[PDB]
């Protein structure tokens, strides 16, 4: 039974936790402890295919969980998340991509660039910049709002689709 | 707002 | 005799203090203690109407003053200030607006978006972005420089005009 | 019959005693012991309202009367008096205002700035300076002469009006 | 530089004090002790002539001031003041004129009839009556308001002009 | 590393201590014993030049400390401080300047005129008076507030710049 | 009561 191991990475407070909880529990969490790293499973149907999603919501803590190590190693796809109203979070993306390429020791890791908080009127990262970055990396770019659930299924499902291609 | 501070 | 209670809010060091002092004392203060919250009065003539301005210069303490609570409650108009060379301060605006709407429990609170430090050549927030944000909010956007006094009377007077409309 | 508790404060010799005696007893006192603190009552009609004025004439001696303590505490309004021919007494006003705000632990204490001795040709404090100070504080400024009774009823009555607003 | 000695006479409360203070100090006095007699000097330019005005504000004290005696004697011109809303004060005028003629022992004393309080809507002495009286005496009649400064310079300056004619 | 010896002089309670402590310790002292004379050092960067400031905070005790004597003699620059709400302190400045010229036996002593307590509403020394005095002396005039840190770095740094010119 | 009121 196909499990997809997804790892959600990005600057603190970009909404990695909010996105994951939205996907899993169908609600929007205003306050999710910035340090808590947790894993979540959900059975979903994507393009008629039932699969298990096994998602690590990283909090970038240092302190060693055996599960987290296994996850970076055996993580099949990575959501690289920034917030569209947080320029720093966007600048950080390259760092996250670099890290993932090093862990996997590969140029071709299934990955989706995610611009979260797209509900906000205070946008500082234009879509074109994000699209240019995604294009340079040859990965999808998806705009999400954890608050309004916009593109939430899309972000995760797109990563699965990226993994499916890669495996095949 | 101040009057929960942040109280859920 | 009309008093207007104005509340100046925004990220630290955007120039809330410098703007207020400019209006009140007609000089530019390069160093005004970031933590000091104070109130100021001035009698001014706006469109031939003499009014008293009663201005709270916020300095976002997390220290509970009964006066500050009363002020947010009884503040009639809010200057939401960012610095045009400070992207973070612009990102923060949305937060301030939200807070004010929640305090006042109203979608129609007189408010002016103020882009301060217009004198600087190092602009990172373009005017059109600020205008778009103000438009979305349906409030005036004014460019100010506390250093040169550009638009200073304008910012405060515009808020008064917003209040006048609201009351009438 | 509503009682108003008024407290007359200011530098020694500015005419706190002369003003209070003028109001109460309708004569100008050449010599009133600088140390003598006392309270006085008078029935007046203010805006058709009959009220009792209960006035503490402060003298700031270093002997502390329980009446004066009660008065600072339970004083509803403060005449802050300077002499228009005494610059130091004007400088001191700020100090008195500070003290009152601390006693009352309130930024909104009914108060009137009083420039006494307006009969004298030797003016050193111009009216605009006094008006600007009152304006900055958002309180009335009244010019009085204890000698010629100019503005005497006015000073006290204005304070009552300030109190009336505050209460209501 | 010519000094002009002016003496202001008239029934109590007609505004002799308020008029003189207006001229001298450029403000309107709410309360001027009815009994206080004082003298005031001011340097003025009247028709391009700089002159010193030396004004006695009479208060109808019987009680002997050496200054007042000397003033009636050496007073060069007399403002005879009534209030336009006070018939008695008008009736008294004739008395004042008589007294002045006897003091000066002359029927040709520079004099101006002054109808004060011209700001009031409650007029009881019509202008025509006052004009008739002034005409019978062959002196100017001037309407003044000490409150609004109406005709104030005019009244005093006209008396100076009367004195100038007399001396010529 | 160049040491600059600065000497802060002025009437008691003008804020020599409050200014010096603000510069050195970055806080405003409510109560600093008026008689306590102390010396303070701080390393600063002024115009890219790192220097030691060696500041004597004079307390004008008529009591002779060997430190203070050495300091008057070896003091390179003098802050002449008044309070903008203290006329007497301004009147004294001339006296201080005279004394400094006599100690140095020189007409060319680096000096800055400092108007302190600019945060006070009770201003009795207008800026133009202070500017005229500074101009007559050919020295900088800086307005300071020890409370809000306004112009504090400015006052001290300006004196250093004055010294730098003098030496070089 | 009044200003907290029903609110918290
Ligand atoms: N408008 C909007 N707000 C979001 C979104 N995602 C998260 N938030 C808000 O910002 C925070 C994001 O969640 P958080 O768990 O702290 O971020 P993480 O550490 O990156 O997982 C929460 O306080 C939410 O209130 C989004 O997609 N849109
Ligand atoms: N270039 C520029 N700088 C400014 C302006 N206004 C204020 N500043 C500087 O910003 C700093 C802080 O001002 P302040 O009002 O205390 O910060 P606030 O609490 O964010 O209002 C001071 O160093 C000022 O000199 C302006 O209009 N233009
Ligand atoms: N011109 C004038 N003189 C006054 C007035 N009030 C008091 N004086 C004089 O100022 C002196 C000090 O008066 P006092 O009432 O003791 O001052 P206090 O200590 O402030 O109460 C007295 O000798 C009075 O003659 C006033 O309103 N106008
Ligand atoms: N309405 C009005 N009141 C005036 C005028 N001149 C004086 N008064 C007032 O008359 C009242 C008492 O009379 P006052 O002027 O003191 O008369 P005096 O004591 O005889 O000089 C005061 O309230 C004065 O302010 C005027 O032109 N119009
Ligand atoms: N409010 C205000 N107070 C000041 C300022 N500068 C000095 N002070 C005051 O100065 C008083 C004593 O001054 P101090 O520094 O000991 O002066 P020195 O003894 O003459 O060197 C204190 O009570 C402070 O309140 C200022 O800029 N604003
Ligand atoms: Mg988190
Ligand atoms: Mg501030
Ligand atoms: Mg007294
Ligand atoms: Mg009179
Ligand atoms: Mg000291």
Image: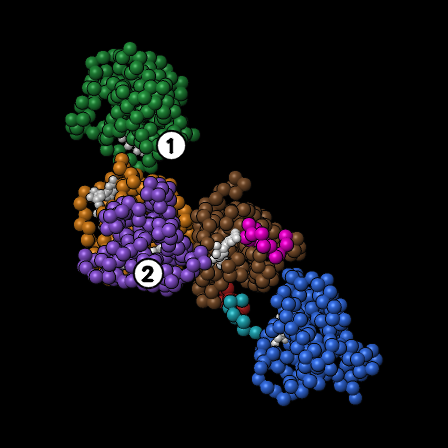
Chain colours: A blue, B cyan, C brown, D orange, E green, F purple, G red
Query: Where on the image, by quarter, is ligand 5?
Result: bottom left
Please determine whether, in this image, residue F35 is positioned above or below residue D28.
below
Residue at x-position 60% and y-position 78%: A60
Q: Please state the horizontal and vertical placement of residue A98, each as a whole percent of the image.
A: 67, 75
In terms of secondary structure, where does tag 2 sit? Answer: strand
Residue C63: image quadrant is bottom left
Span of residues in magenta: C109-127
Residue D63: image quadrant is bottom left
Q: Chain of mark 2?
A: F
Q: For disc 1, does the CB lie below 8 Å from ligand 4?
A: yes
Give the residue number, with chain letter if any, for mark 1. Answer: E147
Give the residue number, with chain letter if any, for mark 2. Answer: F54
Mark 1, mark 2: which one is toward the viewer?
2
User: Would you say residue F10 sits in the magenta stretch?
Assistant: no
Residue A62: image quadrant is bottom right
Quadrant into which the N terminus of chain F falls: bottom left
């Amino acid at each position: 039974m196909t499990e997809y191991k997804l790892v959600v990475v990005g600057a603190v407070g970009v909404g990695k936790s909010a996105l994951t909880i939205q996907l899993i529990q169908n609600h929007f969490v205003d306050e999710y402890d910035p340090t808590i790293e947790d894993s979540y499973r959900k059975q979903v149907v994507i393009d008629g295919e039932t699969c298990l999603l096994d998602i690590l919501d990283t909090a970038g803590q240092e302190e060693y969980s055996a599960m987290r190590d296994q996850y970076m190693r055996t993580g099949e796809g990575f959501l690289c998340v920034f917030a569209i109203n947080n320029t720093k979070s966007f600048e950080d993306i390259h760092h996250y991509r670099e890290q993932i390429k090093r862990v996997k020791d590969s140029e071709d890791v299934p990955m989706v660039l995610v611009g979260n908080k797209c509900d906000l009127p205070s946008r500082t990262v234009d879509t074109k910049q994000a699209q240019d970055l995604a294009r340079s990396y040859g990965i999808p770019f998806i705009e999400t709002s954890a608050k309004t659930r916009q593109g939430v299924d899309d972000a995760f499902y797109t990563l699965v689709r990226e993994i499916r291609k890669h495996k095949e | 707002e101040d009057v929960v501070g942040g109280c859920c």
